[PDB]
Length: 227
Length: 221
Image 1 (cartoon, each protein chain N blue to C red):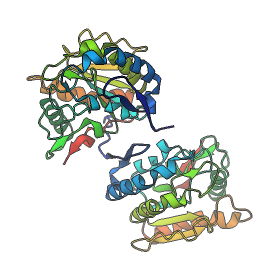
Image 2 (cartoon, chains in turn blue, orange):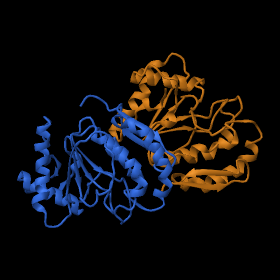
Image 3 (spheres, chains in turn green, yellow):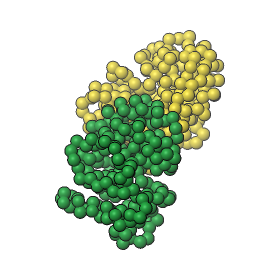
Image 4 (cartoon, rainbow over the protein chains, first blue to last red):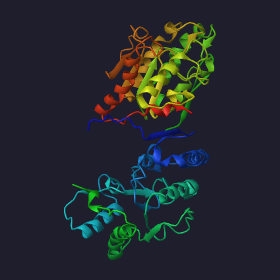
């Protein structure tokens, strides 16, 4: 209020294929020249098929600052269909993962009435997709293309966040992301997994415990609720 | 989709590669260019014919501001509007100075409007006879209207540099769009209006609920 936005923290790079221009918050600058090289190597293979999300939305999460992030909530790749470029986001609130996440937070907070939930509007949380695209309707089908980019980006995230929360024990097998320093990590169940309500609920609960051990402020998960 | 297409024309450069966002005007452009090309290629041009249309390789879907000068540099035009690889041309140095004064960037070696997210720099006429500004208005006439009309369907703000340069252009758009006609970058003693004309583009974008331009993305260090 009073200051006119001028995007002073937003940089951009050119790449050889769609989306041709990647814009990104300054906090990502240390990895972008490597990302450009990797993406130019592989973009041809990626763009052959219809993807979730569309190529113009591959990189929009890089607009998010990292210096104000203390939790990363990470799934393996986008929704097989209707990915928006924002991890876990479902505008019409139909995808099973974000509905299950909302139910968990509802049980943890006591919030009963809501119409949606979005991990991307929570102070201190960056929601993340390890792989930034999938072939339309086929989960993890673009693992081989994103491989080195995914390691690069996750490694950069874990230099900023205090807690990394991975969703899907099977999904995150063998990713080999070489982190530079060990970071507090929880590998929990997939949000759409069956019969593990208690452990899904409790996985979110422990994150704030872990943050306080690190002398970091808790997450207010209720900020994600859409009314 | 988002990819490159191609069309053939009867004269040099014989083939025009373009981003698919331009597809709706390409058959009309071919017809128009074949009509005029012979008269056009008689003279040495800026840029060379192989670079007439390379700016059509830009997407429009990710563009919200068009910065538009009337035609290419009298000499050394690259096909990228305003671009000067050795940073010698007056207009881009003046633009760079404005942006330097707006943003506070002190040290830089160059500036390019073509590397800024959301900006498509543009030349109304895509060529001039070598050494003579506006020499090819007659040839580009209908094409220039066709392309600018198409650009303003995508961008939210159109910024034309040169009040006299753009007098009687008559390019008449299908639907009005937010436009600003400022002074030529090399104009004398109008630093405050030149600096301010860039500043208010972000104000206008905010009104349209569009993301601001970071003009500092143009600097080359």
